[PDB]
Length: 252
Length: 253
Image (cartoon, rainbow over all chains, first blue to last red; front, top):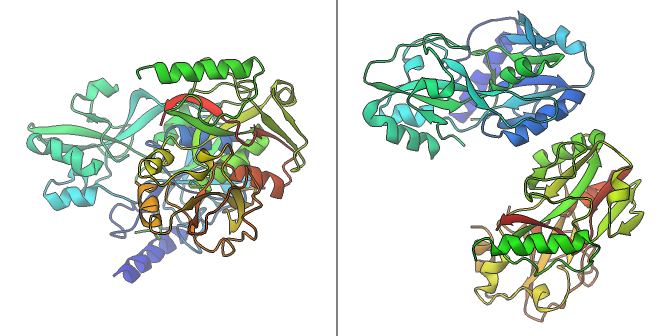
């Protein structure tokens, strides 16, 4: 029921609020999970525009007011604690990981939280068609790669797109792309190298997976694209989630 | 015709650059026209967020980098001069109207331009059902009203949605909305009072139009709502286009 799924959602982030640290992959089936990036209002203008200029890579689910946390995607939730793990960035480099972001969030009083993602998940219908999601078939975090595809810059922000990949068997590629395209369309199909990915076994983010010799790698734009921007643009201070440790919202 | 449409657009923008002032309706047919609101970077955040929160009322066509009067919607165009008429706003009140916003723009070297609009015009489809766009029949701008439907607030900005009104034959209305909905879906049919409109003969924007004894007023979210938020939020300084004097892009509809 829709009522129970929401319960499991309030349940899950309730635990993370209590310090629990575990991947959110398949934590509350049927519940929209989002990526995060919080910036001081000043840099938030750069990212809002970065998001309006690259909606495929940074589709916004919500933007908190300057005095966050709290988001309409989860009534009563606190963005500073309800995420398993946060990546605290300083001067364009990851400075530390933490289970609670309350302190880091205090460094600025006009922090702006951006919840990034899409309420539509193509993974469900794929598995429905009998395709299989390699990383799910395992207790895995989908592998993700920083490509050579430059995003449209905005303000002081600029950077490459980050993609997640799932091996699709040769004869299901066409319908795999069509199913997920029914914004959700794959950005690339095939040759990893054409994306500046020189070794699929070493993903910049997430866990690597195996690809049966008859499988074709397919790539989709994902919400960690913002993290690549933080690193290529030297943003003084930003707070994002740690890949694989997302914010489970109340939206199915 | 191939390229012809955008050529007419370039020419038209050219005359406006050279000081021509004339309603923009009808010119460069087939070319998407847009509303404009230019704000200082600091307020540009509030409005960009106002837009992301109210997409049907403020559909963004483009956003210029701060301090740049250009737009990808028209190569070689200059926003400070290619619109026939501008509205300079001060303390959310409207201080002056000029044929050249060049001087006003220089008051902030961090001006951000927002071209508001949609490339999907439904008027063509209507006139190609005989639904007749009243205001296109008379020499007037489409009546626009400030409603009682508040936009979701964003930062310092707040305000009501400004709708556009087209008189439509009672027995036709059912399709006029279906057509204009292939952002374009109409927000209100009927009692103009229920939408906060007291006297249709008095529109807040454009020219009033005559409603025949049979027609029903049909309303559409209008790309003029930011100006309403500018008055209700006391925006210290802003620049927008004037009534029926829009920016003609090279982007076909």
